[PDB]
Every structure is written in C-alpha cells, then in structure tokens.
Amino acid sequence: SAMDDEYTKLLHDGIQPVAAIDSNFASFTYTPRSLPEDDTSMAILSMLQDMNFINNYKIDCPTLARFCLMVKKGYRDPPYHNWMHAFSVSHFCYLLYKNLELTNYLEDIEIFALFISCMCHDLDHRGTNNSFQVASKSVLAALYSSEGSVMERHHFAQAIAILNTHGCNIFDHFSRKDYQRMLDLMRDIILATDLAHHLRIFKDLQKMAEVGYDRNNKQHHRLLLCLLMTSCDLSDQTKGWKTTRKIAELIYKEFFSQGDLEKAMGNRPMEMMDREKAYIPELQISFMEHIAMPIYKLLQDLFPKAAELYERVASNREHWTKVSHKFTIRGLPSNNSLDFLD
Ligand SMILES: Cc1cc([C@@H]2CN(C(=O)c3ccc(F)c(Cl)c3)CC(F)(F)C2)n2ncnc2n1
Ligand SMILES: [Mg+2]
Ligand SMILES: [Zn+2]
C-alpha cells in the first residue's frame, strides 16, 4: 500500500526544518509549485511545526501524518483544482503568518483554522463550477443546490469526513467548545472560497478597511478571515509572470473541458469556458482588474507589509495587456498553411 509507507516515513523520520525545504521558503517571492509534489506533505508538517500549531495544540503526530495524507489523497487531478493548488494556497497562508503578524489581528485558533481550511478548501473538486453541478443535476447539487455554494459545501463536508475517519481527527482531543469552534471556523472559511460570497461581502470588507480593523470586533475577525482565505486562494497571481501564465493555462484548460461537457449537453457555456469564444487576455485582464487586484488592494490597506503583493498583481495585469497582441496571428501560422481556415 502506497499511503502506508508514505505515512511510515512521514511519521517516524521526523519533521524537516522549513529552511531545509528551500532557503526562501518563507518569502513572498517563493513559488511553492516549485516543490516536487512528493515533498509537499512533509512541507505541510514543517509549516504546521514552524507556526507552533503542533506544540500549541498538542497535535498527535500519528494522527496528523494520517490527516495530511488523507487530505492530499482527497484531491483529484484536474488541471488547476488539484492537491498542488491546495498546497500552494496553504503555503501562502503560512507566508501571511510569517510576514504579516497575524497574531495582532486573529486568535490562535482562527489562524489554525485558516491554514487547515486552506489544505481542505477544494477537496474532491471535479474540475467543474457550481453552475455546472446544478446544470448537470449532479449528486452534489441534489445535496446542496438549495443552500448554494455547492462545491464549497462539498469541500467542507469532505474535510469533515476526513476528520471522522478513524485515526485522522487531529482535533479529537480539543475541548468540546474548541472543537465546535474549529469546525465552525472551517465551515466559514471554506464557504468564503466561493467568489460569489467574496463578491457579496466586498463592501463590508471595504467598510472594515476604511474605519480600520477592530481587534475586539467579532465581525471584523470573520470578514478578515474571509479576505485572507480569498488572498490565499488567488495567491498564484502574486508571483512572477511565468507562474501566472502557467496558472492561466491550467485554469483555461479546466474551464474549456467543462465548456466542452456543457456543449455535449446542449448548453451555451460561459464565454470564459467556451474555447471558441474565450479571448484569454481580455478575460485575464478583466479577472485581474475586477477581482484579483481589488482583493490585494484591500489586503494592502489592512497590512501595509502587503503592498508588494498588490504591486505584483498589478504588474501581472499589465503584462497581459502587453502580450495581448500575440494572440493575433501575424503573417502565416508557423507551418506556412492556411488549412486552419477550413
Ligand atoms: C489564481 C487564479 C484563480 C482563478 C479562478 C477564478 N475563478 C472564476 O470563477 C473566474 C471568475 C472570473 C473570471 F474572469 C475568471 Cl477568468 C475566472 C474561480 C476559479 F476558477 F476557481 C479560480 N483565475 N482565473 C483566472 N486567473 C486566475 N487565477
Ligand atoms: Mg474552490
Ligand atoms: Zn481553491
């Protein structure tokens, strides 16, 4: 059994120091997709140890090894929504902790919940969005369509199922109230990964950033948790252009596969999921300007040590406009043929 021997080494060999993963591992310029996937469950353990969550919460090391592997194996392999997405979303969360002094804004448990939520937040993604679940009358829609945030409810429920698999409940020693609190946090944080929820609360995040964050305001804690989670989720866009170019290819590969399925069901896909209508520079610039850039500008307004992130997102947004001409075929295709016109 494969998870068996991976669990054995991950448990008995010990936790590698975070600096022995990469000497810039804790830096905003690091690209965690560079880490071989075979190294990521150990990196997860290193970060959890480096943030002192293992010690502070007395996590059982056998239980935690089993947890991290179950979570890794709970992801499928679509182009974007796979375990390396969840790993790099988790890594950004760690970066926020190492760079933004989160302990002056959030309780220890909420910071713990964010990280765990990041590992869990796309569990069992099938490469399709919420509209498709309803359109295709999928089992998930039959469970959750009346509540909304179908996939994100499924992600949460998958995280609970992992917690309810014997030997995997890293929380099962918590006080009854702390346990309820952590699962409640995880619900709130995963559900915030629905961009429809982010977009619903944007004015409140705006309003919170303008008056200033009130450490004593419980609703500010929730709002801030949702913004940090979204910032982890879109964090691919805060790295160099090449990362974002590769990530754009993964996303559009995923969307266009969904759009192909929708056409094979008689539905006109969204322009962004239809490979015969999607103009990728247009869409990316729209996504960066209307969604990506405002999230990091809000992150910057709350944490000034986060300016570099927003400036990265803005740089990448402007590189899309620069390379947009390259989607126009000049001269002949490199094979010298115009057969593609027929
Ligand atoms: C890090 C990152 C993440 C996402 C997406 C954004 N998402 C959307 O629904 C979406 C909404 C409006 C858009 F204009 C587009 Cl293009 C997509 C949800 C998702 F697919 F899960 C991840 N993108 N998309 C393009 N570059 C991205 N970079
Ligand atoms: Mg998601
Ligand atoms: Zn995600």
Image: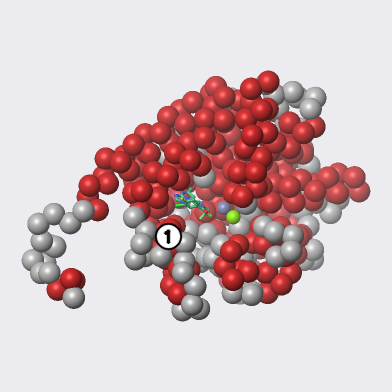
Q: Residue at x 41, y 65 (%)?
A: 274
* Quarter of the image with the C terminus in it: bottom left
Q: Residue at x 13, y 54 (%)?
A: 330
Front position in the image: 290 or 62: 290
The answer to whether 48 appears left or right of 37 in the picture is right
Front position in the image: 3 or 16: 3
Q: Position of residue 277 (x, y in %)?
A: 36, 62
Toward which corner of the image does residue 131 lie, by quadrant?
A: bottom right
5 vs 62: above or below? below
* Quarter of the image with the N terminus in it: bottom right
In the structure shown, which secondary structural element does the residue marked by tag 1 occupy? helix
The answer to whether 232 appears left or right of 171 in the picture is left
Q: Residue at x 34, y 36 (%)?
A: 318
Q: Amino acid at mark 1?
A: Glu
The residue that label 1 is drawn on is 271
Q: Position of residue 237 (x, y in %)?
A: 45, 42
Q: Is residue 17 visible?
A: no
Front position in the image: 200 or 72: 200
Q: Position of residue 320 (x, y in %)?
A: 32, 43
